[PDB]
Image 1 (cartoon, helix red, strand yellow):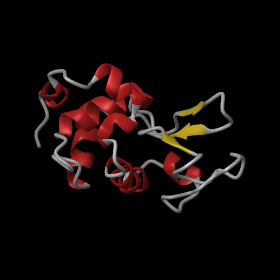
Image 2 (cartoon, rainbow, N blue to C red):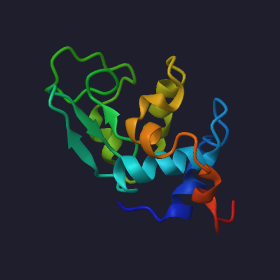
Image 3 (cartoon, helix red, strand yellow):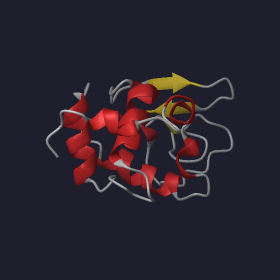
Image 4 (cartoon, rainbow, N blue to C red):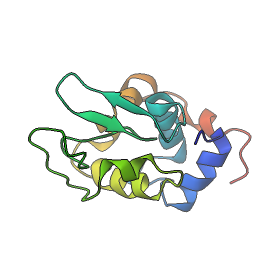
Length: 129
């Protein structure tokens, strides 16, 4: 499923992402845009044998189990396929753990390169939250 910008913003605010760990909703919507382009089925293969899954591109080496990544940890304790669903619940719950793992939102490379230090409130413009 491909979310609309405000549609995703509403879903995220309901799951408690707004200002979570001091990161405004705009940061989360911006991260999702550049990580997966709002597509819940997005999967990207990394050259190290791991794969990023879903709307927030969560990694299979440390966060979810996909059964084919050497040295997997599965810290979110869920199969990576569950991060490819239409409802973002699983992805959000796992993202909450990742963000408080000592690196803030720097964990998401696309956020760091395209969202960090910018006017992120622009990502929630026109949305009725």
